[PDB]
Amino acid sequence: NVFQTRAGCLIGAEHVNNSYECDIPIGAGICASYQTSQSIIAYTMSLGAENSVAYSNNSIAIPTNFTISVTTE
Amino acid sequence: QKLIANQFNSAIGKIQDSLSSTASALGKLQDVVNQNAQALNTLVKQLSSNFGAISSVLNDILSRLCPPEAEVQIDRLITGRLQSLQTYVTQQLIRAAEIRASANLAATKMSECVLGQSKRVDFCGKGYHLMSFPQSAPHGVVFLHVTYVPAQEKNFTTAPAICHDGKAHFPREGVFVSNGTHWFVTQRNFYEPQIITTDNTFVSGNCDVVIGIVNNTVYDPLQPELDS
Amino acid sequence: ILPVSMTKTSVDCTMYICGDSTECSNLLLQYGSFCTQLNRALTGIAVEQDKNTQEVFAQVKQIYKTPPIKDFGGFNFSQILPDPSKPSKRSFIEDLLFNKVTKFNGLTVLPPLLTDEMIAQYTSALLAGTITSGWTFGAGAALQIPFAMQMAYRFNGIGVTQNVLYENQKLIANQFNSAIGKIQDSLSSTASALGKLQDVVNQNAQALNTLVKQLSSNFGAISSVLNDILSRLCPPEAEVQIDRLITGRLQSLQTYVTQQLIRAAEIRASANLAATKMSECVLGQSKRVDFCGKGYHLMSFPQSAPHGVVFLH
View 1 (cartoon, rainbow over the protein chains, first blue to last red):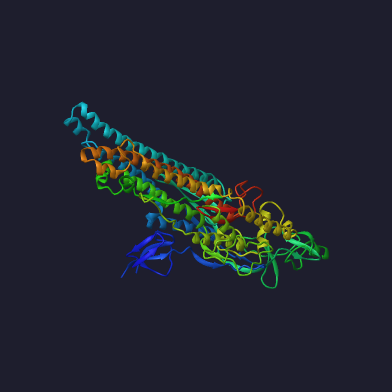
View 2: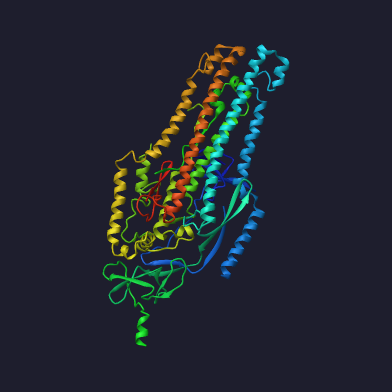
């Protein structure tokens, strides 16, 4: 419940070993969020899901189907 | 065409549901409203400040004091109220430059995404851009970027070239691929396998030059006519 | 080389102007919301530096990683791929770039949201997606393709027929490997190359040092030290002297915050450019002349640098 971040001492946030998308940005990789009896947790933010691309000198992936996406800017 | 139309109609339906449910989507336009409101509210509230004068209210100075001292108390207010305007106009000039950069971007997305088909990656949304539709919004614009996203990969064995009778054949469009036992040629962005032919391929030189070339027959459509 | 962000600052303008004097703090309240709108502007600048950094690097949706075997058709990416030897897994060129770039008074520096080790994971992911899957990881899933066949697509994209690649593949690979070697040699010698990033550090440092130096100015008061006025004078005259220090120190902050707002707009324009270079040069193959370097663009590799990005076009 008392945690030394590289941004400073954080108090009242539960330090957690999981990683999630950044909810509230604290700084230097740390974020906090409200989660499940609930508490404000603090965690190192996740950059994304990890992916080993199936590369080799003679393998290619080709899409057999598509999706039309509409995205709003 | 029915699949593509149904996927488009479904994706436009998801825009209605997203915008109907989720008011936080418009945050860029609502924040530009909030910044201008907060700036005018701050400019009004700074009238209540004394700036070292005997009162925040100009008519207290003009009712309590006569001109030899009243002008010193009024100049304290003029100094702070003019500094209050100069701060507001400076921050509105900087905020107007931020909005002009955003309007120049929106004018560029109108020309390139709506009036055209941009080749520029992620300029007109994620995926290969097909087209875009403009929709008006308070103090802004919304682009509904329609894009092709490739969706169901299969792995194939592939080759840069095919050896036929000592000649190296390359694809005119697309790539060579194998299901495991047969070789085909297909467009790069959608699996549509074709027989490898002298029409689907061009020759250049012999088999020795190319790293990873494979032996396969290349069909010549003239040969069965001359057999016939 | 492109600036992407700048040092995030917060200035506690009550501590800058009044130095923990309550006598001055009570006078500073008579200026109203000038101090809260200075903090509001600097906080907008500071949050934008994280947004500028996020929009350049966080374009890749997944942390793509290269396979163990580096069979890239003869092209050698080892100087631009992550170095496993290191506590932060920067590439060899990202280590060169990080080496070539180099206030109790309420002034403070806040950390960036993404650490250099997180920026290096994003440039690693962008680069590993680019090497293993071409432009396809920008349009959807990373579709793997052999690197020589990706380069043959890049050659068709500049109107050079793809057999010209396969018939010259060793020459093209050796010219690439040699040209990456010249980047290490240029960075291991030419300290002025990073000057566009170093100038952003220099301008921000020079503005903060100017803001500190203006505390030494009298602005017409009997002393520039607020504890001289408070230890020598008493309220009828002390408030006359302190209002000269408040006026000049508040004008000193309004000058600093105005010039940081104008400089933040310059860095944001450079981060929007760098984010567009990431999408169109790294996630794609730009047809735009001289956008992705001189010559017909084949591909680009991002490398992180202090407060910036470096594209190897």
